[PDB]
Structures are given as structure tokens and as C-alpha cells.
Amino acid sequence: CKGEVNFKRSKFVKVPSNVAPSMLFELLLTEWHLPAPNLVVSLVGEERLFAMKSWLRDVLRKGLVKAAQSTGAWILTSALHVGLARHVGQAVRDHSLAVRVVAIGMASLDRILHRQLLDGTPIHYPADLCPLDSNLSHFILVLAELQLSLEKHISQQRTGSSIQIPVLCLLVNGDPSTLERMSRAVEQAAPWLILAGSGGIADVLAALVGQPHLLVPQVTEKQFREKFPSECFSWEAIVHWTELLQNIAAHPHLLTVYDFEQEGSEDLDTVILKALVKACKSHSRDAQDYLDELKLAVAWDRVDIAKSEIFNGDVEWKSCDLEEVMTDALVSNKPDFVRLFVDSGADMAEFLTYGRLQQLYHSVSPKSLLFELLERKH
Amino acid sequence: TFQVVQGNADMFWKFQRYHLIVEYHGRPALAPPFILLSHLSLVLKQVFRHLERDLPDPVDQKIITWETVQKENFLSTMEKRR
Ligand SMILES: [Ca+2]
Image (cartoon, rainbow over all chains, first blue to last red; front, side):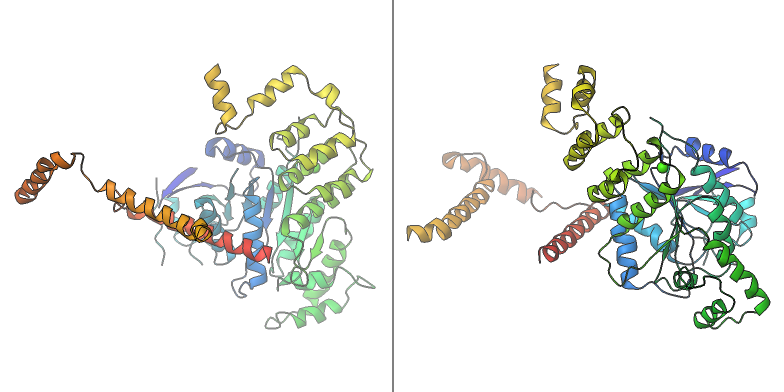
């Protein structure tokens, strides 16, 4: 049941739970004609109680999205709620006003206001239970099972020349319930990035990933008493969450906690790429599996990390498979990478044939002068 | 004086050029002896009845925002150099 709301027409699809994710992703791609994503990051925090500090806003939005505007990605931001969601949404629109970054809003149809009017073709939605935003341009209206299964589907489908799609999760000061949402997520093999100064459950998590005895019989009670003390908790409820934490902390490779206020020198893209490579290390050591992440590095122009982490000597590279990324580095004229690829084992002797050279010459930017010269001569 | 002119009077030359440009822009096509027709025609039209032109709200607003972004980039660059 696809429809559009002409507010600025925004599309929406009503989907019940346990629906085949493949059908959803394919309907998205075809009927909305959205570009293939080179990255997807899923938000996990929305608490309107605590405002966003400076050190958070500046980097998290400006420094991250200004860089991501070069390669584009998807943002699985929760809609129909009040929080940083509308901030990020309008931020993307203001950045585009000046490869694209888009936000997809998914939310349960019950918590929305004026849902009968939408269920019964732009359904007028002027709103003074919580009302819905009119900034986000797309809606997947129903839910945690859907988000988990859709992440499992995206992290698996191969859109490549056969390359994967990287997935990442960004936890920003969430409520205790999200614990469950994260628990099974560790089984789903998707790297988590936890902001240590966020100020929700991210705080207690950042604290309790490293301990002498990671088992938290009552120190978890101590932390939950320390942070957000307005909410009292039953010991019988705790005795379960502590086991949840004891299970989650049993996979250190996936999750990574990071602090931004102490030394913000490392921008967001650096830690994102670092966590992605750290997670992809544990899975396998094949040549092809590293390609997607590697491509992302080329888009960020981060030679030092690609040299330290990828080309450390673990993955044995051959001259056969570096051709695609080599052409991608040539066309984008990043020369610090071409030298690295040549030294890593690639050869210009067998790679460059007259067909490849014609393909390179076809790729001249249409605005440039050589383009017009060759076109006029032809 | 030359050296003074190498800087300041060279700037004046440009200043003089700008003044001349505006002066000739305001002149009509007819020559000194032919002005007797253009001035008369202009006076007749006035008795009977460029730089100044500006855009609309939408169009202009984009320009203003773009300039703002440029200024921000400039300041951030100055800070980085600092
Ligand atoms: Ca990969």
C-alpha cells in the first residue's frame, strides 16, 4: 500500500511485521528509484529529555555529513517522535540546498497520531501519542524485529566486480529497553559504535565494557542508580539485564566504544572506518571481502589507515583483483593511492591496454576543456 | 612619485577606468553633432509619459544562503591556518 503525502510530496509504505525483507528492499529500490548505497548507518537513540551539547552537534552532524556528502549513504532514523531526528533531517536538507544522503523513517503505526485518517492520495497531516514530522521524505510505517531483519538483509546482499554493502549502528544515549534491541544485534554480525559521552545507556555501557570481572552482579545496579536516578528499578528486573550485559560483552570485536570530548582530533569518518575494518578482520581474510571497506577509504582519502590496517600483511593481494579499485583511484585523481596500489603488487605493464586507455579517456569530466576539444574534433 | 604611482596611482588608473566605463555606459549612441536628435527624442518621450535590476524572493534567498556558506568556509580556513 504505497502512497504519497503532498505537503513536498513524501512517499510512504505501510508494512506489517514479519514481512519478507527482500520484497521491501526491492520495492524501495525500484519504485522509489533510489541510488545504490555505499554505506548504511542505523540510529539507536532518541531521548528528547537531554539536549545535545556543542561537542556533540558540531562533529556529529557538520563534520560527519559534510564528508559523507562525497560518497552518500542511508540513515535509518526513527520518525514520528520528537528528538535529534528532525535536527538531522533538516540538516541534510540544508546541506543538499548548498551521491546524496537520505533518511528513511520507520515507526510503528499505533503510536502515530491521526492514523485512521491516513489509513482511509495525499492524506492531509497538519498536526499542532506523538505527532509525525513533515521533514523526512520517506516513510516505512509498521518494530525492532523488522529493523534487525532488514539490517541482516542489507549486510548480506551483494550489489557489486562483486562488492558488499557495509552496515553500522550508532548508539546515542538510549533508554534501557534498547538493550534487547542490541542483544540479538550481536548475533546479527554488525559492528556497533558507542558514543561514550552520550548520556543515556551509552554511559553505563562505555563504563562496563572493561572490568576486572565483567560479570555485574550488583555493580550494574550501582551504575543504574548513578545515572538517570529518577527511575527506580526492581532487583528482579536487574538480575536479567546483568545477564544481558554478560552476554553482550562476550564479543569484543564487534562493538567499539569511543570518546569524543577528551580528544576530538579523530573525526567520525576515521573511527567509522577503523571499526568497520576491525569487524571485517574477524569474519574472514579473503581478498574480495575487504574491497567494499577499501573503496570507502578511497572516498575518504585515508591512506595511512588503509596502509596500517588493510595492507598490514594479513591479506595476500594479487594483481588480478586490484584493477577495479585502481581505475576508481585514477578517475578520482587521488595519486597517493595509485602509488600504494602499484607498490602492493599491481602492475601498469599488464593492466593498461588500449581498451582500458580508451575507457580512461572516455571518463574526462564533461566540463573540462579536453572534453570539448575531442568532441569538436570528432 | 612613480613608485607611489606604481601602487596608488595604478589603483587610480583602475579607478579612472571604472569612472570612464560608467560615463560611456550612460551615453547614447548619437555623436556630439547628432545628440540634437537623441536628447530631443528623450525629452519628448518623458513629456509623453542593468546594475539596478534585482531578482525575486526565491532566487535571491538561495544566493544569500550560498554567500553565507562561503563566508563560513572562509572563516574556518582562516582559523585552520591559525
Ligand atoms: Ca566487507
